[PDB]
Image 1: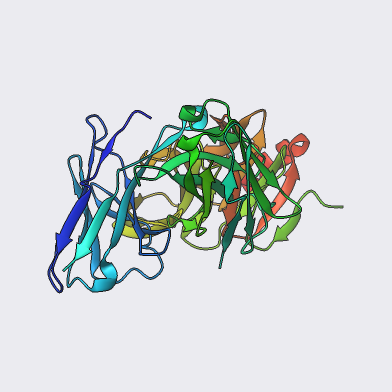
Image 2: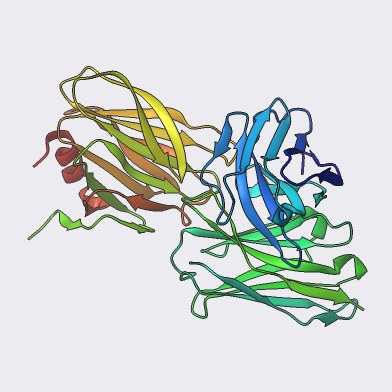
Length: 235
Length: 162
């Protein structure tokens, strides 16, 4: 997890004004692209836009208004909202890929709380889990066949601290990349015939209390697709 | 009674190992995109003969790219754009100068093999990957399937056409 993403915890703006949310990369990553995510009240994150130093990369997310623009220069990456509406009050998250093949990691910013003055994924879980037990989560997918072979499936949790944490990703063949911070406690599986994604996390602790999200990543497009998450509370 | 199995409708799929995909380009633009989303990203674009320096828009993996393109030859040019990581930029890796408008791609031996050079002397070249099995492709043109054991015939086609 070599790069670090810095987001201010909070930002404020008045109706109809403009505001620029920013995400600052650590030194040595001036060329990196970042994804912006919008987490509306009572919702999980959704994809907004991808930006490098040359502006937006790929298509913006579904439901993103034309008031949302995006820019980048140096280590700064910026999401600009003009003519702010109250539905723009939300939490905004910064994410970035790092590495390729076996050493791949995804890093996230702390999140910024902005206050204003197809393919479907459904995650299921136990709700409550006692410590030292094994957390078992599943996610059903309805938009595509998991045997198609053009999707990478990520799991991302929101624990204490309120910032997103990438925990792993699995490919159609069953090959995986896990976050090293989880030791080897995390195993991820794909059920080709039931169209299901499954997750096991051994020896859970209060540190594992979080909302868990499954995120589809289509090979040939930029926008993500998130499930709405499964709450997990460790006794 | 066929060496050329096809032609097949343009499609998106994970090709089996040890089979040449012989892709027949009809018009200029993206011919195919292929990736495993880990360490391999490639896209071939087609430029028609006698095109002076001009700027063209291409969609690569859902991203708008504006490339300056030159083709002074009497033949078509097929440029391979490659990148090896998510944060990487695309760069020109290979060029196929061909009047038969055929490209080829093979997954074998843990590598991806394509044709490059100028017909009728084009040759195969390899790209290393650590995840061959997850490599898929969107083919924008009709295509044929030839087994690797018949690569000689594939070669001839790419170099000489039908």
